[PDB]
Image (cartoon, rainbow, N blue to C red):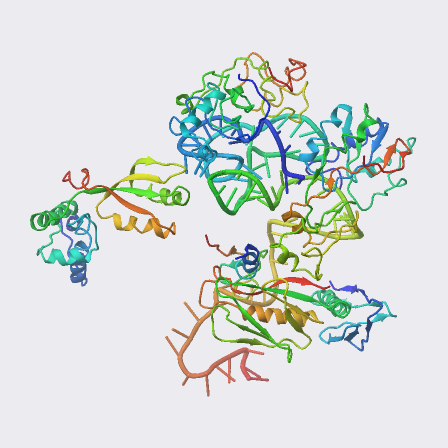
RNA sequence: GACGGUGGCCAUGGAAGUCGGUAUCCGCUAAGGAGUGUGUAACAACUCACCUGCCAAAUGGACUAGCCCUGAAAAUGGAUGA
């Protein structure tokens, strides 16, 4: 019991795997959180920062917390590159009849404001969304509806994201 | 209580939801409105020109336009004006919440509002008028000073007004 | 055995044997296609003068009433083996009942398997045909002839009566077309008396 | 495209009732897989529709 | 329990004559001859004069009791095929590609090209009592007609089975030649 | 046949039997859920509950446990001894 509580978890034959796969799970999660590009901001995949985090030469430690480690990898590329570290906002336009089952899918998925629905015209709603979650929401409102639905930018920077530096 | 008139030439058969402060939180259907040829600001006051005070948001009410005007007509429902005169005030902001009805007697309005929908409702009158609309709402009671449908079976009011209103 | 289950016949027989001895002149009707929309608009006229009373082949429980009454369930006309009936009973208006009971009828298209009343006319002719709905009628067995510039078969004489079912493909020709030739409703069969027959003649008027 | 032809064509290869062990089409008023692999099992669902 | 006797009765119409010789029923009608053996039953098929034909079974239990109604209804099928033989109606449903259909009358075969835009030609012979012809009146429909139901419905089922979309989602495409009507006259 | 009050109350672009929280009585009858469902701007339309028409005599269910079948896949060829 003394060895269990006042010890540190040493590692078996799978140490090299449970450390290398751990430090390759860590870069495949904490680096990819909220990151949009330059030039009328869009998100992108994980492998672009898997290039651009070895390119900034990050060495990953685990004893600093994962949220703090998220706030550490984007500090270096705010220092280096021109990237944004906040939320964004969108103005979803959807037609009334064939878009309500698209409404109630993302309404318990993400936050909404300005729910302005008509009968004759189109449902216009505004969003409270991270920077990276847009590429899902560009496609899921077409692959369920089956028609065209419009992506209109609202705002490019809102706080209470990672801008509070938790 | 506006008076009921005969049908006219080229009647615009309409259906509305509200009658108090119509379209308060956009509480009218904006598709039953402009389908018939009428603007929206014309259509909002139509809900109050027929019943300004005793409308409620689930209705089989009817509004007719005799070469398009507000004619002070009442081809309204039999259910709005019986739970309207319980707790009397029926506007739109006080139809955002629940209400417990008033137990103030309405046997002598349940013969004039008895046949507000159709002329002859295919129901046996003069002996069962209080066992159809006296029990039409189990929520609350008409008056707590008497118990319905048993000291209300043959104990009736009005021999000339059960089919025709005032 | 009997007298059990849901919607008991022992609470219907209090109407089916007791008020069936308090009436003068009755109408043997036909309820073979009659609605409840068209029924509620004729059961408010009869309600002041009489009733709309039928047990529907529970009525051979009327054999115990025929001791002194001598009421026939099988000895009169229309021996009650092939049809549905809902007989009309009256106390005040035993006489002028045949005029409001044969007014409230509605003309409508028939379907497949309906009991086929005495006045059915197949929709035919130029007004009873579209050039686009020919290909449905071009599906059937009977070959068509050209009369008045239309792919159509003409049959305007009565060929079917009560007791013969209508074919399935004939129903859409009545339903899709606006042709409703006959206004049908209640059909009086026999004018029945308390132990005999008052009028052994038919009168749809 | 006539709707009656779509109804007829769904009558023959869409309106079925597929057993759960035996992925096998049965008629829409079935209660039992007709095959030995199922165990003549009385566990079966409708064929799913489209939108 | 096996019941002592379980019979049925088949009513022969006056223009039809059955020639049964030991579980080998042979109707003869105005329009054609038809025959089928029932040698897979312990059954005494036996006719009463001219109007009746009485399938009987002494001491059958089940799988044997169940077969006398089957071989009664098959003789009734043989009878109805030789008074007013069956005529099936088969309709073409397609999404985009108009199905072409060829028919000769050597073996009365059907040939189904441009089915789903496939270039394979679906030549199919009919069973040996059967002819068929296109409906000039109703569009996109071929009517089958014959003397026996086990030949006619099986020919129709072979047309229908060989007119399927493979390697796709059968709930959407629905291109084929399906049996619509099953009339007699 | 499956009707009315009624599109029951509430809630909302719109929710009218049929997305949901609550009640669940009546007229007329043989028979009506303030609705068992499909769909829709909600309806409409089709549909089931329950009754009734043809019919002619036995019908339906929840179990029990005998045999049998599914469960039940292994390497040489194969073993109720054949």
In the picture shown, does residue B92 fall above or below D31?
Answer: above
Along the horizontal axis of the image, is D18 left or right of C23? left
Whether residue A63 appears in this view of the structure is: no
Along the horizontal axis of the image, is B31 left or right of F63? left
Residue drawn at x 13%, y 48% is A83
Q: Say which quadrant the N terminus of chain C sits in.
A: top right
Near-viewer residue (E108 or A157): E108
Residue C21 occupies quadrant: top right
Percent position of residue F60, x then y: 66, 50
In the picture shown, does residue A21 fall above or below C173?
Answer: below
Percent position of residue C155, x then y: 75, 53
Near-viewer residue (E60 or C38): C38
Percent position of residue A39, x then y: 16, 49
Percent position of residue C107, x then y: 70, 40
Near-viewer residue (C188 or E103): E103
Residue E176 occupies quadrant: bottom right
């Amino acid at each position: 019991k003394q060895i269990l509580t006042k010890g540190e978890v040493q590692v078996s034959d799978k140490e090299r795997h449970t450390q290398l796969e751990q430090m390759f799970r860590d870069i495949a999660t904490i680096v990819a959180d909220k990151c949009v590009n330059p030039e009328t901001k869009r998100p992108y995949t994980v492998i672009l920062i898997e290039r651009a985090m070895k390119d900034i030469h990050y060495s990953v430690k685990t004893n600093k917390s994962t949220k703090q480690q998220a706030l550490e990898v984007i500090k270096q590329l705010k220092e280096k590159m021109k990237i944004e570290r906040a939320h964004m906002r969108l103005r979803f336009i959807l037609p009334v009849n064939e878009g309500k089952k698209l409404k109630e899918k993302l309404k318990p998925l993400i936050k909404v404001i300005e729910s302005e629905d008509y009968g004759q015209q189109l449902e216009i709603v505004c969003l409270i969304d991270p920077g990276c979650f847009r590429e899902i929401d560009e496609l899921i409102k077409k692959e369920t509806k089956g028609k065209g639905s419009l992506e209109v930018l609202n705002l490019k920077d809102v706080e209470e994201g990672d801008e509070k530096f938790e | 209580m506006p008076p009921k008139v005969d049908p006219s030439e080229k009647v615009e058969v309409f259906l509305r939801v509200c009658g108090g402060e119509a379209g308060a939180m956009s509480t009218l259907a904006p598709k039953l409105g402009p389908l018939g040829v009428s603007p929206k600001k014309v259509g909002d006051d139509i809900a109050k020109a027929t019943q300004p005070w005793k409308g409620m948001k689930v209705s089989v009410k009817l509004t007719i336009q005799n070469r398009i005007a507000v004619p002070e007509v009442l081809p309204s429902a039999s259910a709005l004006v019986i739970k309207a005169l319980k707790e009397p005030p029926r506007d739109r902001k006080k139809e955002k919440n629940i209400k417990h009805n008033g137990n103030i007697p309405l046997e002598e309005i349940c013969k004039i509002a008895k046949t507000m929908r159709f002329k002859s409702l295919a129901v046996d009158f003069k002996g069962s008028v209080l066992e159809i609309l006296g029990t039409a709402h189990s929520v609350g009671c008409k008056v707590n000073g008497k118990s319905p449908r048993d000291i209300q079976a043959g104990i009736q009011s009005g021999e000339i007004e059960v089919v025709e209103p005032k | 055995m009997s007298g059990a289950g849901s919607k008991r016949k022992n609470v219907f027989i209090e109407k089916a044997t007791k008020l069936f001895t308090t009436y003068d002149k009755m109408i043997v009707a036909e309820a073979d296609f009659v609605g409840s929309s068209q029924l509620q608009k004729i059961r408010k006229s009869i309600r002041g003068i009489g009733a709309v009373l039928m047990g529907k082949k529970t009525m051979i429980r009327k054999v115990i009433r025929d001791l002194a009454d001598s009421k026939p369930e099988l000895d009169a006309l229309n021996t009650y083996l092939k049809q549905n009936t809902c007989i009309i009973f009256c106390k005040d208006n035993i006489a002028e009942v045949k005029r409001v009971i044969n007014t409230q009828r509605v003309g409508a298209p028939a379907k497949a398997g309906v009991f086929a009343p005495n006045d059915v006319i197949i929709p035919a002719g130029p007004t009873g045909m579209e050039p686009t709905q020919t290909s449905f009628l071009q599906d059937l067995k009977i070959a068509t002839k050209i009369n008045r510039g239309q792919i159509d078969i003409v049959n305007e004489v009565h060929i079917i009566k009560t007791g013969q079912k209508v074919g399935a493909s004939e129903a859409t020709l009545l339903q899709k077309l606006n042709i409703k030739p006959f206004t049908y409703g209640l059909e009086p069969k026999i004018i029945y008396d308390a132990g005999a027959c008052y009028s052994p003649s038919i009168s749809e008027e | 495209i006539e709707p009656s032809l779509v109804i007829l064509a769904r009558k023959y290869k869409c309106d079925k009732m597929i057993c759960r062990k035996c992925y096998a089409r049965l008629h829409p008023r079935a209660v039992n897989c007709r095959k030995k692999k199922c165990g003549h099992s009385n566990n079966l669902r409708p064929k799913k529709k489209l939108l | 329990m096996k019941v002592i006797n379980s019979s049925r009765k088949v009513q022969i119409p006056e223009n039809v004559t059955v020639d049964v010789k030991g579980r080998s029923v042979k109707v003869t009608g105005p329009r054609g001859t038809l025959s089928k053996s029932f040698d897979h039953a312990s059954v005494d098929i036996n006719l009463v004069g001219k109007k009746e034909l009485t399938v009987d079974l002494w001491f059958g239990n089940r799988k044997q009791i169940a077969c006398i109604k089957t071989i009664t209804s098959i003789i009734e099928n043989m009878i109805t095929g030789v008074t007013k033989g069956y005529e099936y109606k088969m309709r073409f449903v397609y999404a985009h590609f108009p199905i072409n259909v060829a028919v000769t009358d050597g073996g009365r075969v059907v040939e189904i090209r441009n089915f789903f835009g496939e270039k394979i030609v679906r030549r199919i012979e009919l069973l040996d009592g059967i002819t068929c012809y296109r409906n000039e009146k109703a569009k996109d429909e071929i009517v089958l007609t014959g003397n026996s139901l086990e030949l006619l419905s099986q020919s129709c089922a072979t047309i229908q089975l060989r007119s399927a979309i493979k390697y796709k989602d059968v709930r959407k495409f629905l291109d084929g030649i399906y049996v619509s009507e099953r009339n007699v006259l």
